Amino acid sequence: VSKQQYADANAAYLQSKAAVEQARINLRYTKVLSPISGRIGRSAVTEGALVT
Amino acid sequence: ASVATAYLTLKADQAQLQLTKDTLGTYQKSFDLTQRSYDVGVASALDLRQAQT
């Protein structure tokens, strides 16, 4: 194959590897992690509540 | 009639030789452009081999 075809295939592979990381970010957002370390209060919402 | 036939045959085949000599130069220029396109990296060896054939 030519070098331009390999450059095109590498560009498409890297764009897909970035899109799957964009998906992993939102998948990591559904497990909402504690941003800092400290004492946590009470939960203002319970199980079954809809958030936005 | 035989002398006239052989003379016209030679007259035709010299023009055939000149026209094939032009076609060979056309193919040579096309191979040079394909070799340049392969040496810069846009074509592959599969096109270079066809232009060689």
Image (cartoon, rainbow, N blue to C red):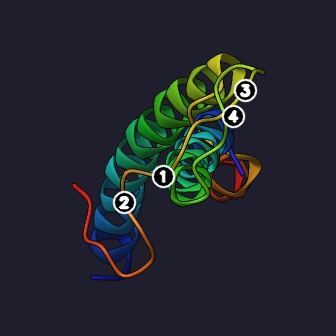
Q: Secondary structure at mark 3?
A: loop
Q: CA distance from mark 2 to mark 3?
A: 17 Å
Q: x and y percent of residue A2 in the render?
A: 67, 42
Q: Earlier in the sequence, mark 1 or mark 4?
A: 4
Q: Nearer the viewer, residue B12 or B33?
A: B33
The residue that appears at 41% across and 45% down in the rendered structure is B23
Amino acid type of disc 4?
Lys
Q: Nearer the viewer, residue A41 or A48?
A: A41
Reading the image, the residue beneath label 2 is A45
Q: Nearer the viewer, residue A17 or B48?
A: A17
Q: Earlier in the sequence, mark 2 or mark 3?
A: 3
Residues at badges 2 and 1 in contact (C-beta under 8 Å)?
A: yes
| Subunit under mark 4 | A
Q: Is residue B13 left or right of residue A13?
A: left
Residues at badges 1 and 4 in contact (C-beta under 8 Å)?
A: no
| Subunit under mark 2 | A
Which image quarter holds the N terminus of chain B? bottom left
| Subunit under mark 1 | A
Reading the image, the residue beneath label 4 is A3
Residue farthest front in this picture: A42
| Subunit under mark 3 | A
Are marks 2 and 4 in one subunit? yes
Amino acid type of disc 3?
Arg
Reading the image, the residue beneath label 3 is A39
Reading the image, the residue beneath label 1 is A43
Are marks 3 and 4 in one subunit? yes
Q: Earlier in the sequence, mark 2 or mark 4?
A: 4
